[PDB]
Image (cartoon, coloured by chain):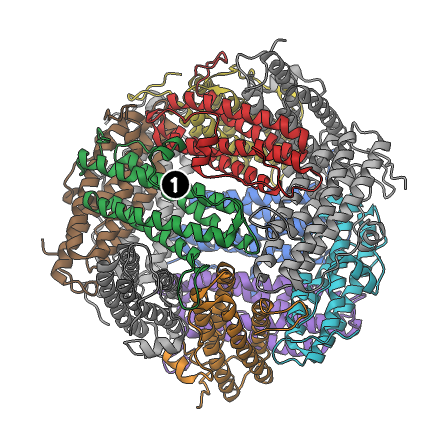
Chain colours: A purple, B orange, E brown, F blue, G green, H cyan, I yellow, K red
Amino acid sequence: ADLTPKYTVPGIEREAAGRLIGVLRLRLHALNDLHLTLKHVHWNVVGPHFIAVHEMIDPQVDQVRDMADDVAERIAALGGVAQGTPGALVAERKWDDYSIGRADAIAHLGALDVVYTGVVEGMRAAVEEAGKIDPATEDLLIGQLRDLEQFQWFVRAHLESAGGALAT
Amino acid sequence: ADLTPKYTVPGIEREAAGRLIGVLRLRLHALNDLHLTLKHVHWNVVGPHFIAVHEMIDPQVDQVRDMADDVAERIAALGGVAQGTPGALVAERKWDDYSIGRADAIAHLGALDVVYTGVVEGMRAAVEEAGKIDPATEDLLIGQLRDLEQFQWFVRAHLESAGGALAT
Amino acid sequence: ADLTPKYTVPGIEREAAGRLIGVLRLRLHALNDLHLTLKHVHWNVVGPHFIAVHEMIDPQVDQVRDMADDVAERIAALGGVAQGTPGALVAERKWDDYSIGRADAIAHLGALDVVYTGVVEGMRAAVEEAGKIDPATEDLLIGQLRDLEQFQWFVRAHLESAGGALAT
Amino acid sequence: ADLTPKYTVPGIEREAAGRLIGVLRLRLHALNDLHLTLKHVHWNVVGPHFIAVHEMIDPQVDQVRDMADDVAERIAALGGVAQGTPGALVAERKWDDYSIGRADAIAHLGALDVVYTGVVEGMRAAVEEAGKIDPATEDLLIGQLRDLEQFQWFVRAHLESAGGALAT
Amino acid sequence: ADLTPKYTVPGIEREAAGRLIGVLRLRLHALNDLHLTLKHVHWNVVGPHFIAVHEMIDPQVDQVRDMADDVAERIAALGGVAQGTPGALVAERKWDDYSIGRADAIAHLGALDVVYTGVVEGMRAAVEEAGKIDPATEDLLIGQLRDLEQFQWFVRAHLESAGGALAT
Amino acid sequence: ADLTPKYTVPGIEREAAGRLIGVLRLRLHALNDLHLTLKHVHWNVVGPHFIAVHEMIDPQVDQVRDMADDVAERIAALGGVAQGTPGALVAERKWDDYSIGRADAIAHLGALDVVYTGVVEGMRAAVEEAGKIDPATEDLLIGQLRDLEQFQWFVRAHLESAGGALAT
Amino acid sequence: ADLTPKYTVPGIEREAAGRLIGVLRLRLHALNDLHLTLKHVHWNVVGPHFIAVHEMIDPQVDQVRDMADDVAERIAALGGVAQGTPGALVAERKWDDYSIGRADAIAHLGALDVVYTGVVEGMRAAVEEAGKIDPATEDLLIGQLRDLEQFQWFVRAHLESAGGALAT
Amino acid sequence: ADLTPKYTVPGIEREAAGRLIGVLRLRLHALNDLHLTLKHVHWNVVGPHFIAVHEMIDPQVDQVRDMADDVAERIAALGGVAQGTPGALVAERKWDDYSIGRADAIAHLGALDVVYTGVVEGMRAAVEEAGKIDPATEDLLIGQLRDLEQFQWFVRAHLESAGGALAT
Amino acid sequence: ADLTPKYTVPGIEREAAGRLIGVLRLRLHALNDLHLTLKHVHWNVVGPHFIAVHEMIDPQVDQVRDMADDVAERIAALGGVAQGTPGALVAERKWDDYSIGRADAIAHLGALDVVYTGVVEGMRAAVEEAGKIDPATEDLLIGQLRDLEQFQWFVRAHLESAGGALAT
Amino acid sequence: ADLTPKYTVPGIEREAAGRLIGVLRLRLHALNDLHLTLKHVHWNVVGPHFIAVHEMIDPQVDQVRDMADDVAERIAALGGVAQGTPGALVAERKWDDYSIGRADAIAHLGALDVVYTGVVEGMRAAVEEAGKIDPATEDLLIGQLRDLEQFQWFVRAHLESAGGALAT
Amino acid sequence: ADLTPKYTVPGIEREAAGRLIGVLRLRLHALNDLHLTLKHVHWNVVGPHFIAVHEMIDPQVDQVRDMADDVAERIAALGGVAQGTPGALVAERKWDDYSIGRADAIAHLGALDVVYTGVVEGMRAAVEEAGKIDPATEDLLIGQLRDLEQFQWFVRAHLESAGGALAT
Amino acid sequence: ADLTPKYTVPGIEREAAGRLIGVLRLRLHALNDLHLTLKHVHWNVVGPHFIAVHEMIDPQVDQVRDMADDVAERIAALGGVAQGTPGALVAERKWDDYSIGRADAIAHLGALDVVYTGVVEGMRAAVEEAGKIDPATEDLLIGQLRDLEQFQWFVRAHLESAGGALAT
């Protein structure tokens, strides 16, 4: 439970850095589960929109792996251990595996819209906790939050009507 | 008048997103009018500083078109319509056409200094409204605001005396 | 009404250059309204063909902005003022705003097919006027005309049946 | 009928190289007919999946032209003549012209799935013959075989159901 | 015989576009037979000028494949079917297969000089027909014609005496 | 247990492809657990060899993610589902989580040497099974196997004595 | 006087090609004298606009050297000798040396405006002669003519008043 | 003492901009002293970790020079003088010269850890002052602050034990 | 004589790895002697085919140095010492120095054809030994073997008659 | 005073290397003060030549930082300490701070002309001392000397009359 | 006759700089006549070595134009006028026009060998004069001299026998 | 013994060029033995500094191969034979094979420090001989000498104490 480090970034108290490390450790499991899950969707989409969807996920895979790197190294700068192994991720995460195997591209985009709502709400909660402890970490998380919301918009636009309502 | 959307980014209430969409819709007209107006200046500057000024505007044209893209796609992620047609821009804008045709480069930089003061003050007002609704949109607008102020500094430096006063 | 310049390109009479400047000034409003309108479509397309259409417009936006630059600088070389501000564009243009807001990608491609027929016919009329005044301007416009017709073909191919007929 | 060369790669008997040259001469007609046929599909696909399919074929055109180059130069290193003219291809091939003209993108992907099954089975037969004569040629053909099967998977994924069955 | 399309480029009558489609369909067979034939020469040249000739053909292969792409897509924009399969090419062409197998590089350049005279004269005839129907297609063909004549000059320069006469 | 697909690559029987899919599904969990574990080591190495080790893992992370992509897409071409989610990986894997948190770089290289021996032996077993079913899949796995053994050599070289013995 | 070649481009009569060779031989002296003269200006401009002018000439030097290459190789394809030595240029040219040594940048731009009027009028005369003999050569010269006129516009813009009149 | 400018960025009062100019003038001396000091360390590190440390500083030198450029130009946009000369830096700074000459790489990393704690605490103090005056300057400084803390983490990781404690 | 290592790649017995190390140690002397000998030819070719031959060897020098690197590092991964010094190469090699000094390009290509037959036969013998010990090493050597045979084909093509016979 | 090192470059006596180290230590302070001073000018130039001057300094900043790196590493190879901290630079230098704050671009170029005369004369004196001790160091300094004189020429050209006299 | 400048590079007396300006003015005519003459050869070589020779001259054209730029700008830094117009070149040069029009590639290489002997001897004489006046100019000319001699070696190697004698 | 050539670079007497050829022939054996020996070290370094040392040698391998190319081609321009075969190198060299097989990275850097002292002293002796015969060759060797001494400094820095003394 106690992640207070032995040293942290100058200007931050160790006990406050331990609670920021705990916030970022769960956000790192979320980002690692999200890029594993985006590659799963990339491999297992079918149907007449295959190539478009398959190609559209690949730059988001790369962007999310970059976000996970930068959260992990911020954990390490704050004096903590960035836990990246999948047994830890599955033991500590607060959401279930993505549940779609092979499916049409539009069905996967519906399920990925729900994945991204969980991730965006987790990041928004983490921004608010980080803003009370360290503005440099808060700033890193706010830029990531906006990029994740914009890729959820590309997913949602495929499900959206001319009148601006979402199917899935 | 009412731009409340049917869905918006997770974590934001729809009525608050409608008023952020309205703020960003006017900032998008300002950014589109600004890159049209920078190309107009680029084409219609003359006199002995032509090539320097002509070349100096071109990367700002590109940067401002990128800013307009990112405001437009943030409107769409918030559930709104990014209106990009010039009849709408002219109907909804709260400033007049840039009024200089062919002129010396230093005369155009004087008039563009006034254009950028309007744009910078509009963006600063929009930062303050967005900061009450969504920190991710506020962050996007603050980085744009600083870039626009820095390009206004390149315009102003041409008009500035050794004692640090501005001509135009 | 009278756009006869004080100097023009060697070998061209000033009064003939004024009427070529008038032809190119309207073609420049058309090209500026077209790249504003292509970005509007890019931002406001939805439905299951979103990413494909959204991505397909972006290189045409860039190509049309390049065409507008080269018409504007040819106006300036002919001794005229390339008017690039949106109030002038809306005051002088001979067509209405693009009328589609958010819509499915296939609906926008129908409406953009009609936009491009207006632009292609305007450019073909301008080629024929320029060919009587200056072959160098005629040549610039003919290459632009073919590129615009080829991008209208990519729009039309989405609307076309196996038997070679167009829906919209 | 007899393609025994006057010299061949060190370590290979000339009569065995002549029969490998005959195997590779037909595989070269197949690869040349396939990249001509992929460009034909690229030009003549229509309907709402146009741009995605049109763009997806282009890197496979390039990859298949590279495969044909490398089979041809291996024929020449083995002491034979790589016949690349279309009258020879049509006289010696053991399959018919691709039979689809203009058609929807999904209809062309159905017919291209059948083209690729012929090509993949021809390459697998050629791998087994080359493996008895020269492991260096067998290795070249096995890497090509896998790349062709992976591009047939991109074609098939467009035709595949969520339960993993193929339409066409 | 009748290739009148159901739609064509704005400003062109359908019956005139059908006869331009027929002109460009044969020019596309010529360009496809030429890049197949240039690769054949590339693979089957021998003797002490091998590497120079072999390397010199490769950028012309790429340039001619680009010319075929642009004629094909202009056929499709004019409302026609760009026929790219080799059985159609051999059935409809008005010239014979290139007749040289393995040969010295200078012998192949002699035979390729004759191939290019046929192609250049076919393109010049097509420029004159296109100029009566559509200046945009005429312009595309004139630039291709000059590039093909310049690569025939590189072939001819190898066969030319100090006094400016051609051997083959 | 039964992964026989409804279609597979031409030339392969479906029941044999199901058992190859099962072999590759476990090799894909191994490659995904390995690149998650390499990033974990990258973030959590300390001590005087930090930067060298930290930098040396990064191209292997990229190479292993590429290997996982190519195994996954080969599963999909063979007619199977490439399972990429971490709950499935942890449920189906036949090895335990990497057990080192923060540690000196040389301690992590000792533990990663043991990880790579498991991965290399799993890949060598999979090469031998694939070689009985499909040479194209066997070839993909043999190239991956050699690359993984070469990166294990870079890990082992740090642990090796001048006399060629390994510490850890 | 007589430059009729022994061979020329297919489709052109030799006597007509000799007179086109004579037209292009003088246009090649003009383009070679122009890029020598642009480098002379680049080296010998002074005063407070030095760096801007000095930098602005360099891409035009490169563009004009490219124009000279393409006229020379078109002379050679037409069967003639592209004479590139400076004693021939000075013996055959119909204009005098550029007469400005070291001078302020604005004085050199005045004198270069007069150089470019001679070059543009020579090219326009050559376009009209080439259009009667060969459309492929006419097309090459028209694109060069427009590029030269656009760089003369950059020179003239430095000399131009807000009312659109030229000083020098 | 009084740095109130004659003009400043729109929306900021001049007296408040003078105190922000004073904050940023000292942060600019700190960033210039830091990149001079990083190059000093790069040149004067020795011992068995030489190349790793020497190479690791070079991208941070480049990043810190970029940070100094952007603080300086923000001073100039706010209406102030960015003082970059070393006599001013040494007269106005509030810290002493870096005191290590030639030394082992690990000794220099100990001393650079102390340099970076001073710089990070100075930047955090400047973020808090800028946040009361102008959010655009505050945002620039927060991103710089995080990058400096992350490079201090790379320095500290070399000094850190497996249990997460720092030596120097 | 005994090169059995203390450790080797997982899955390979040490005594079998020692005999593979001995096979690869001689193949590494052959590849190092070959790239030294290709540079010798590059420097010492003369006569009218100089530039073509001189340029054609340079990418093969680079490719052969890459082959030597990859054999050496495979020796090291198998637990052996990759001996790269020239006294060892000359003591252990089973062929004589290349014997041509300055000579015409065609004479050097004759002698290099004989060098490559020795190298290709040595590599084919090594493929067959490696295939009994380790498929990963066998695969590396088979790809190298084919590349070396293809560059011997470029050498032989210069010596080959139209009827497909070799001079030297 | 005594900088004789414990080792130096082979072939140089230690006492002679100590006096070369002293020469290069002062040339390194001069080059570091010059690139700090060029950035100061870049930030603090104003008036109608701003952008041209501002842009023209930036590649010289980069070139001078490269010169300082190469002098510093030559000091270290000669066995000395390259002192890079600003307190040492200000204590040991033999010239005063650059004295211009904000000023017009032409005023700064006058003062920078005087800075460069000091630097060029210091480098010429150092070339003559190095030529008596070590030709490799002399060669490095002569190339730097010429580059510095050429950038002083770009500064002086802005101040020079048509008759070749300098203002400032 | 008298080229003493009004200012020159620091450390050089004006009268000595005038005589160095005269040396470099003639070396600049030689380098400009040489790159005009290399392009002439490039355009007018024929026969079976055409492409090799034609391609081999092009990088030397670029290198010689760079040498002329750097001599010209060194003249300007020394206070002189770099005369670049062809009437001056022909009036002041001390050699005749290159005398070969269209000719076989080997005949042109013979004549270019004689051109380069004149240029190399002129540069060697200029190195010796510059070494008495200014080591920075001497150094620039020595590097150019070696590059010109190495390109003369590529020309001579085409004319050289196996016994090391030159034909032409 | 006698290497007087039949022709040499203009301005050099043949007998003096023969003795420069002999000097450069031995410097070429030294540079070829050095890049073979650097690759040997790269492959056979072990222990905890492996990756840093292994990576640090690779750009020096490339730089030394470039130095050998440029000495060889200067031998050929001087009229001599650049002998590149390893039997000649071992017969003519005046030093022994590098004697370290597998060893820790720091042991190899000790032995490579001694190799580089031999090479640097050989190059310094060759500079002094070349300076009496030809300044262009002397200049090439002086730049190589400095680069080799700087890479010996990177080797020595790993062996150096804080007080500036070398271990090995």
Residue type, mark 1 in image: Asp
Question: What residue sits 53% from the left and 26% below the top?
Answer: K150
K13 or B27: nearer the viewer: K13
Residue under the image location 63 percent in, 74 percent down: H136
Chain of residue at mark 1: G
In this view, the residue in front, F72 or K31, is K31
Q: Residue furthest front?
A: K1
Left or right: residue E141 versus residue B62 is: left
Say if I23 sits above or below B39 in the image. Answer: above
**Horizontal and vertical percent for residue I108?**
46, 18
In x, y percent, where is residue K39? 40, 34
Q: Would you identify the image quadrant in which residue H98 lies? A: bottom right
In the image, residue G164 lies at what x, y percent? 39, 66
Q: Position of residue G88 (x, y in %)?
A: 36, 31
Q: Which residue is denoted by mark 1 in the rendering?
A: G96
Secondary structure, mark 1, is loop
A162 lies left or right of H99? left
Examine the rendering and report whether any part of residue G129 can be seen. yes
Q: Quadrant of the N terminus of chain I?
A: top right
Give the quarter of the image for residue B146: bottom right
Q: Is residue E168 left or right of residue G105?
A: left
Residue furthest to the bottom: B1
